[PDB]
Amino acid sequence: NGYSGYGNGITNTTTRVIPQVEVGNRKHYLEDKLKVYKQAMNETSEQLVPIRLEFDQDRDRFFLRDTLLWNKNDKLIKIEDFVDDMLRDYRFEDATREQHIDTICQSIQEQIQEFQGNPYIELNQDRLGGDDLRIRIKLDIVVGQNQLIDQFEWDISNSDNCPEEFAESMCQELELPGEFVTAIAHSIREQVHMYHKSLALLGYNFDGSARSRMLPTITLDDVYRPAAESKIFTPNLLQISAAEL
Amino acid sequence: ELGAINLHALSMSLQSKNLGEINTALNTLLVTSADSNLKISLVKYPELLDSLAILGMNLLSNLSQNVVPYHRNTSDYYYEDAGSNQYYVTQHDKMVDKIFEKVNNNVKQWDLLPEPIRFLPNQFPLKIHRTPYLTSLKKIKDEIDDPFTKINTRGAEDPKVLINDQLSTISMILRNISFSDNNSRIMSRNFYLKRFISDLLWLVLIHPENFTCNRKILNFKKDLVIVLSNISHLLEIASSIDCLLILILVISFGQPKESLTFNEFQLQWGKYQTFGVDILAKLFSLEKPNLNYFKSILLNKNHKDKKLLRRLLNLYNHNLLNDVVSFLFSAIPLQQVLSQSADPSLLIDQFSPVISQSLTSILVIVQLPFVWLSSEENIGSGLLKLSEIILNINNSYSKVLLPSINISCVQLIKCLVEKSICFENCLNNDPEILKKIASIPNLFPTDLEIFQLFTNPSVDIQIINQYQLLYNLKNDILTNLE
Amino acid sequence: LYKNHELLKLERKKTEAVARLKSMNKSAINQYNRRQDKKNKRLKFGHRL
Amino acid sequence: PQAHEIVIPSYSKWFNLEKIHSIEVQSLPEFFTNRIPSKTPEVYMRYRNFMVNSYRLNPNEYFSVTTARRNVSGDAAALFRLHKFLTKWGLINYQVDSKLLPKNIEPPLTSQYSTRHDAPRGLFPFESYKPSVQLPDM
C-alpha cells in the first residue's frame, strides 16, 4: 500500500532491511541517551558559560565568528559531536579535517577551563539584589546589515537578575528579531564574567572596594538623576553601512 | 513474508499506544523469523533493544500489578496551558503573584525510567512452579479440547490474554534476534535487557497466576534458555537472585523420581536439557570473582534482597547443589554405551565435554557441615568404558576426543579423593568407606590394561600420566586400607 | 576461555612479582646510596675539623 | 496564513502544539523536577512550538539546531537535546526531501467495495421461508 516511514519514505521496494534512513546527511542521533540522561540530570543545575569562536584568521579558512552558551555542569555530550553537528549545519565540506574539528574543541575546552561561574557572590554570599558596582556595560553587535551600540549600568554583584530579560525587553525595538538577543546576553555573560573573574584573581568577592583598575571602572553613588549629555551615551541607534570587517 | 523493509519501526514501538505496539511487534517478529536473506544488522540499532526491554518491563510490571494499560481517561498527562510567559518568567516577580493572590480575593523528585524490579509489595515469594518438563502433558491437558478449553484461540476479547501474547511475541522475537554476531550488541551491556531477563525470571518462577496457557510458560522458559545459549559473557547484576533463578531454570528439565534424584534422560525427545548445561558452562566459565562466587554463596544453607535469598532456600525444603550434580549427570550415558557402535556417539559426544568441564569446575568449588558422596549404586562410572571407547577410536568429530577422555579421568580422581578427604575431615563415617570405595566394578582400570596401553598408541603421553597417577592412587588405597 | 582466564590470573601474580621485585630492588638501591652518603658526610665533617 | 501541505509519521499523532504528553517528559525530564528555576515546562513549550512552527514554515528545506541557537537560547545543551529529540520524532526536519512514484495499478484499489464474505459485524444473507409469515407480527 502506501509508502511512509522516513520523510514520505518508501515502504514498497525489493523487501530489504534499511537502518534509520533519516539523515539530512549524517543525521540520526538518538542512540544512548536514556539511562545516562535520567540518572544524571535529575539533580540540581547551576551556572552557564559564554563562548566565542574565531577561526577565519589567515591561519585557516573559515567563517567561524559565532558565539553560544554552555553548561559546564554538564557531562552528557561528546563536545566534538556537538561541534560536528554545528559544522554540518554550516553546510561545510564534509571533510572535517581540512575542516579540522579538533582545533575547535580545543579552543572550546580551553575557554571553558577558565570559569567559576559567579564567585562566592553566589557560591556562599547572598546580598539582596547584590551590593554595588554596576558596570557601565558597553555592547555593540553587527547583525544582518546593522550595528547597535549601548552602554548602561548593570550590576555584577547581584545574582537575582539574569541577562535574557534585558534581551527580551530591548527586543521592543523595531523588531530586534531573534538572532540579536542571544549574543547580547552572551556578551553580557561574557562582559561581566572576566571582571569578577579578574576580581577572582584578587579577593573582594566578599568585601567592598578593591585594586587599582577597579577604581576607574565603576559607577558611583549617584545620589541624583543625571544630565542629558552624559546618559546621552545610554541611548541606542540603528545604522546601515557597507561592511569592512 | 514480503514488503516489510524499514528498521526504524522502533520509533512507533517506543511510542506508548496499543496500536503502534501491535503494528510493529507483529511485523518485526515475522521479519526476524525470515532468514533466507533476512537478518537484522547493527548500525544504529541499539535503540531497538532498549525500547523492547522497556516495553516488556512495563507490561510485565503492571501485569503483576493486575492492571490493563493503553486505556484510561487521562491523556497528554501533564500541564497544558498558554499562560503569562514569553520565554523567561518565574523570577522574583513570581512572589508578586502571591501578593497579587493575597489581594485579588477581596521541587518534585522524578523517578527513573523503568520501575523497580523486585521488592514489589504484592509479589511476595511463595514457592510455586518448580515442576519438570512433565508439564508438557499438563500443557496437553491444558491444550486438550474440552467444553471449557478457555483457549481464546482468537484475539483479545479480554486484555489479559492480550498482555500475555504480547509478552510471548516479544520473547520470541528476542530469541530470533539473538542468533549472530550482534550477540556482542546483546552482550551483557543492554542493562535494559538484563533488567528484563531478571524480572521476567522473578515472575515466571514466582508466578502468582496471571498467565493463561501453561504452553506460554513453556515457550518463555524455552526461548529464554535459548537466548541464554547465545550469550558467552558476563551476567548476574544484582546477581544472587538472578543466579538462583538461572539455576532453577536449567534444573527445569530432566525427570526427577540420599542418591541421585534424576533419571538420566533417554535421549530421543529433548534438545533443551542440552542448552541448560551449555549455558551452565558458558555463562559460568568466568572465574571473575562474581559468578562462581555467587554460586559459592549458594553453597550456604536493598538489604531485604538478602532476606529473599535464604527465604527461597528453605522454601526449597541438607543441601541442594547435589541436585545440580545429578542434573549434570544426564544425557551422557546408557545410550551410547548401549548402542551398536561408537560412531553415532560422536554427534552427542561433541556436546558431552562441556558437561564434564562444568562438573570438574564446580568441584574446584567444594574443597563445613555436609553429607555428600555420589557413587552409591547410582551411576557407577562407565566413564572408564567410555574412555576405552574413545581410545579404541583413536587407534582406529575430532579435536574434542583427547580432552574429553583426559578430563574424564581427572574428574574420576578428583571426585574420589575429595569424597575421601571430606568424610575424613568430618570423620562421621567408618573406615568402611575405603572398603566401600574398594567395591566398585566401574573403577580402577586393570593393571593389564595399563600395561598394554603403555605400549601400543604411544601418542597419549599426558593421558598416560593421567592413568598412571590414577592407578597410583588405586594401589595406595589398596595398601593403606589394611 | 578457561585457559585464557586462568593465564591472565597467573599473570596478575606474574605482574605482582614484577612489582614486588621492582620495588624491593628500589629500596635496596636507595638504602645503599644512603649508606654511602652518610659515610661521605661524616668523612667530610671530620676532614673540615 | 497557510501555504503548505504538512504530513507527519502518524505514530507521532499524540503530539499537540497546545499541550504536553507523558512521552516527552520521560524522554526529557530535565525540565520537570522543578529543581532548576531557570527551566520550566513553560519555556520548554515556548521553545517547542517556536521550533515546530519554524520548520513547518518552509519544511521543504532543512532546519538546524544551530539556527535556533542563533535565534533564541537559554542553553546550548538542552536546546540541542530537545532539537535532536524532535528530529528523532520527526516533528521537525521530516519533509526535507521529496520522493515520488507512478504507482501502476493492481486488482485491489481504494475505490473497490463490493458484496462478498465479510469479517465485520453481523449480517444475514438468508431471510425467511414461507411459514415465517405465519406469525401474528408486531
Image (cartoon, rainbow, N blue to C red):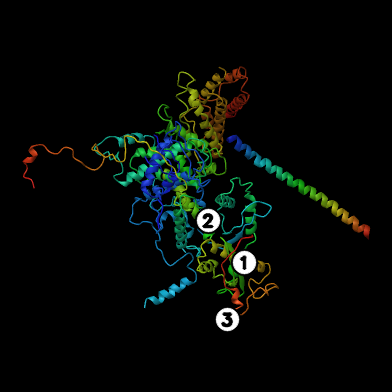
Q: Quadrant of residue D131?
A: top left
Q: Nearer the viewer, residue B379 or B64?
A: B64
Secondary structure under the numbered disc 1 in the rendered image: helix
Residue placed most toward the observer, D53 or D104: D104
Q: Residue at x 9, y 39 (%)?
A: D132
Q: Position of residue A193 (x, y in %)?
A: 62, 66
The answer to whether the residues at label 3 and label 1 have Cβ atoms under 8 Å apart is no
* Residue annotated with mark 3: A225
Provide residue D93's location: percent of width, then percent of height: 47, 50
> Mark 3 or 1, which is nearer the eye?
3
Residue carrying label 1: A191
Kindly report the distance in space between the C-alpha atoms of the residues bearing marks 3 and 1.
Answer: 25 Å
Q: Amino acid at mark 3?
A: Arg
What residue is disc 2 on?
Answer: D67
Alpha-carbon distance for marks 2 and 1? 24 Å
User: Disc 1 marks which amino acid?
Assistant: Gln
Please, which chain is the residue tagged with disc 1 on?
Answer: A
Q: Residue at x 61, y 69 (%)?
A: A138
Q: Nearer the viewer, mark 2 or mark 1?
A: 2
Above or below residue A38? Residue B169 is above
Q: Alpha carbon of mark 3 to alpha carbon of mark 2: how far?
A: 42 Å
**What SS does tag 3 mark?**
loop
